[PDB]
Image (cartoon, coloured by chain):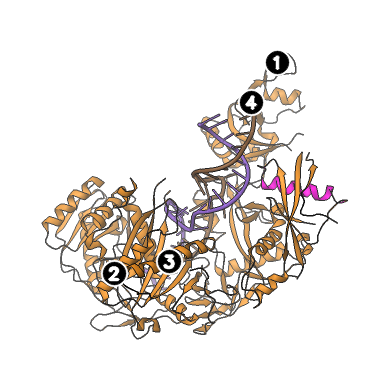
Chain colours: A orange, B brown, C purple
Amino acid sequence: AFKPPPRPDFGTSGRTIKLQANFFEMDIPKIDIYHYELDIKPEKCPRRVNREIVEHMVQHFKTQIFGKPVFDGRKNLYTAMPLPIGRDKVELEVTLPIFKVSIKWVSCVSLQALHDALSGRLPSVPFETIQALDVVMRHLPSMRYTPVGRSFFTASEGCSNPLGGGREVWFGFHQSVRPSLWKMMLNIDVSATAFYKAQPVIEFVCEVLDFKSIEEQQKPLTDSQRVKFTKEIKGLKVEITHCKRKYRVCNVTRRPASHQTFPLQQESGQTVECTVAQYFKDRHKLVLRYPHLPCLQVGQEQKHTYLPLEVCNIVAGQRCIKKLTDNQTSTMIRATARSAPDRQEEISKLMRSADFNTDPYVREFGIMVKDEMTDVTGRVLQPPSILYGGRNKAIATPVQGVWDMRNKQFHTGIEIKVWAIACFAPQRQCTEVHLKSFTEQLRKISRDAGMPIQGQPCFCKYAQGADSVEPMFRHLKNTYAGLQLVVVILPGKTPVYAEVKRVGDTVLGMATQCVQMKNVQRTTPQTLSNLCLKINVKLGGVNNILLPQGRPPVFQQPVIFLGADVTHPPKKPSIAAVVGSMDAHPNRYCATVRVQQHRQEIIQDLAAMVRELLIQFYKSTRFKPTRIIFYRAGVSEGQFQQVLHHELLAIREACIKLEKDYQPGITFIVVQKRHHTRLFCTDKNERVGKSGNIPAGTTVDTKITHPTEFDFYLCSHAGIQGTSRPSHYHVLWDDNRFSSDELQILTYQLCHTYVRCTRSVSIPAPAYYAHLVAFRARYHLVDHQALAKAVQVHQDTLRTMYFA
RNA sequence: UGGAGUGUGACAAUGGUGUU
RNA sequence: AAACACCAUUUCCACACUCCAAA
């Protein structure tokens, strides 16, 4: 439970399709770079200030040292060539129009060892080296561009994209140095956001108050205009233009600049009441062109510092946080999240205009970055045949990641005979005609799907308030003998839903299916169809199964599939969810949920949860799992060592405390949808749909993947909009010795066992379900050992997929 | 609360050190 | 205790959009 397994082989299954990844090949020398620790007092200075101080320190000490270093922004410094130092601390002083800096030697970072790591020589890739390289590549844009989070943003060179108000669209990119099979690469992905336009505040007023010009009104702002302008500018920073000095607007004056007064404190004799306009006329010899406009209150309210709008400009680099209107959000997405070819060209254009090969700090370390994206082979896996079981038992073949139930019926359809209707929406906007039409349409779609509604509902009443839920359900459960479903019509976002699921899933164990109000008024066969999918699953039926004869050889022996996800509170306990397959299809899943420490992603009580699932598996299959496939979802790379250490043992522990010496093979896999890796089709004819993304089933385990360990990218879904995010799978452990092809096909096949739609999903079904179970348990909570029993679902609910 | 996809948040939340 | 800086963590969740209902 310490070391992750090496990649066994390279996959050869599926049709090859020429691809390009957003990785850029780097040429790195064999030179050893020198690392030094800095010590700067005071110890609270911002990163930008630190880089500024170091920059001054470089040029002012050229006679002694620096015969061109890079900086972290925080106490870490690197140089290409060595300098006159030692292990001893070298302290000096600098001045910025006053700091004390101490430079200390740390260690040497050899890039020869990096080549040994990328080659077959050394197994471990030095993290300190990756850090150093990343600091180098980020040193210039950290000062040249505007850093946001881990990305760098900037304005537009030519065409300035506006948004209205004081906002505009700034574009940016996220860079990161990553190790590869043979050569180091630079991962880069573009993005966009909204910044405040660098313009005079007098024009900011014009754009906010919808003025063509400022001379449109000579009369002062009405109270509504003052509030509106204040709402937009309160908090922003502005620079002055009659001396430079940057200020922060805390408020907007009520009175005009001609009447706004303040304590003048003219040397001796203390304060005299003076207006702002008179001050700028006397002191700065400036007559106000627009004295009828209010002033910007700056700094401390006790300080009484005011500024006329015509001497203030809004400083650039200020990202917007305010709510975006319809036109703003539209223009945003109408300029971002574009199609795959568009994003592709954007990254290419970026890599062209960024010009890493001409920047001095990059050239200093003799680093060369390829200006073209990395070509990668890639291969599209073969979609599994989905077997439906009507009278004809037709088969659905996933075309482009999507299939349908046309002339097809469920593998195991349930004859719904007893069901109820409880509408919580007002009857005024939801008539009985709507309910009957919805009933007719549902009955038709249901019977066509293989899950026939044998007749009208035994119950149909309007209601209101969450307090009506728990009592009514009890009455419903005691009145009608053997009801199968309770349909709850909701008028939108309401606390009613949470209690419906609480009473339904935990308290009584009644199969409930909520429907939004609008879908009852106007009904489309597609919506009702997907709804039927949910119902049939919630009632214990089987929508569809994988083709038994068309499965990887792992199914030849009893194997259980596990999915795990963790959800954290907005101080409240977190909840971890672990699901497990309960048949050999694998269609049916059982859910286990626990409560945990705040924001602890490491599943603590996992062992007991696995034990429950294993026992339940045996009770449902009469077979003991020879294999365990654990799809962990939600953890990042920085948590791997921790998670893999505890959770793997927790799984193994559960297998020991259960029965004798029963130790099946555990395959620990980490699913990751959140990463800056993009994939594009090289051939224009290979593009799929409007979005023009890679075809569903695209598999990549070369060039852009880990040099030694077992990982692979798998785009298992078809891109509906924008650019697809290929789900990354990293095998942290494997006792069963899976081959690349087998595990990838198995994963891609489990992406077809999703029961809520007739499509291929981005992540495997167990991981998706586990996320659903967690997010469902989120509603059950709405003192620790008390709420611990709140997530404990019903006895009869346990044997079902309520989370669907 | 029919479903899937992908955009935004990073002056975010907390515990920590520290400031007139 | 009120703001304000910085260090290590937290991709949780929220909102929005697109498509399945046209030919």
In space, the residues marked 1 and 3 are separated at their CA atoms by: 75 Å
Question: Taking A202 as reference, is A732 left or right?
Answer: left
> What span is in magenta?
A43-62
In space, the residues marked 4 and 3 are separated at their CA atoms by: 62 Å
The amino acid type, in three-letter code, at marker 2 is: Ile
- Please give the name of the residue rendered at 46% of the width and 73% of the height, measured from the top-left corner: A716
In space, the residues marked 1 and 4 are separated at their CA atoms by: 14 Å
For label 3, the residue is A649
For label 2, the residue is A615
If you read the primary sequence from the N terminus, does the residue marked by circle 2 or circle 1 appear first?
Answer: 1
- Please give the name of the residue rendered at 62% of the width and 70% of the height, measured from the top-left corner: A124
Q: Are marks 1 and 3 in contact (CB under 8 Å)?
A: no
Q: Are marks 4 and 3 in contact (CB under 8 Å)?
A: no
Please tell me whether mark 4 or mark 3 is closer to you in this view: 3
If you read the primary sequence from the N terminus, does the residue marked by circle 1 or circle 3 appear first?
Answer: 1
For label 4, the residue is A303
Name the secondary structure under disc 3.
helix
Please tell me whether mark 2 or mark 1 is closer to you in this view: 2
One can see residue A804 in this view? no
In space, the residues marked 2 and 1 are separated at their CA atoms by: 85 Å
The answer to which of A651 and A309 lies nearer the viewer is A651
- At which x and y percent is residue C15? 44, 52
In space, the residues marked 4 and 2 are separated at their CA atoms by: 71 Å
Name the secondary structure under disc 4.
loop
Location of residue A655 (image quadrant): bottom left
For label 1, the residue is A270
